[PDB]
Amino acid sequence: EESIKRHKWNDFAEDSLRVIQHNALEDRSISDKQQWDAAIYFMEEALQARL
Amino acid sequence: GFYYYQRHFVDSELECNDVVLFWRIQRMLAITANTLRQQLTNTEVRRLEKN
Amino acid sequence: GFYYYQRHFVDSELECNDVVLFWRIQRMLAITANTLRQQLTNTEVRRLEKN
């Protein structure tokens, strides 16, 4: 209990993540079959759960 | 589906662009998890040990 | 394939920045010519008649 309360996460991460996240999204280019299949896999998984 | 885009055929309904979104989000999940892990393992976990 | 260009997987795969370059300058030259023509025919020719 105590050790948790004496720790805080550095809030600046929120801004760093904002940049980093954008960069990972920024790649919109599926150049070949392998990434095409990975992309279709994740799309199928995410949509199948909601379906 | 790959021929349609080589040929630019006009009667082709199929356009596979949702694939790019979920590819991007999969990679963004990976990048966010990894950045958070690195912040944890080099900055926050040692602060936790001190606390 | 313009799509092979869009892939941009590797140099061996089609890397047609050349076609898009010559297209861009196609647009530049055509629009410059038409702008010059328009100023000529609606502004400069009537000024020429007055002079």
Image: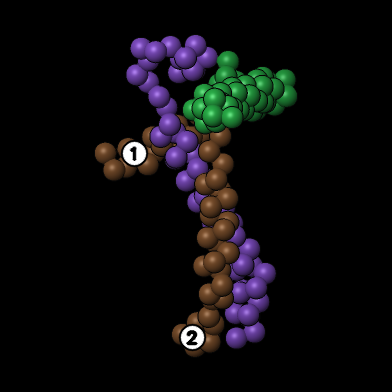
Chain colours: A brown, B purple, C green
Circle 1 SS class = helix
Of residue B50 and residue A38, the one placed in the foreground of this image is A38
Residue that badge 2 annotates? A5
Is there any visible trace of residue A11 in the rendered image?
Answer: yes
Of residue C10 and residue B30, the one placed in the foreground of this image is C10
Mark 1 residue type: Leu
* 2 or 1: tag closer to the N-terminus: 2
Residue that badge 1 annotates? A47
* Gap between marks 2 and 1 measured at Cα: 39 Å
Residue farthest along the front direction in this orientation: C51
Mark 2 residue type: Lys
Circle 2 SS class = helix
Residue in the picture at 48% in, 85% down: A5
Q: Percent x, y for residue A10? A: 56, 76
Q: Count the marks: how many?
A: 2
Q: Percent x, y for residue C8? A: 64, 28
Q: Chain of mark 2?
A: A
Q: Percent x, y for residue B12? A: 37, 15
Q: Quadrant of residue C12?
A: top right
Residue in the picture at 52% in, 60% down: A18
Q: Chain of mark 1?
A: A
Q: Is residue C4 above or below residue B41?
A: above
Residue in the picture at 52% in, 14% down: B6
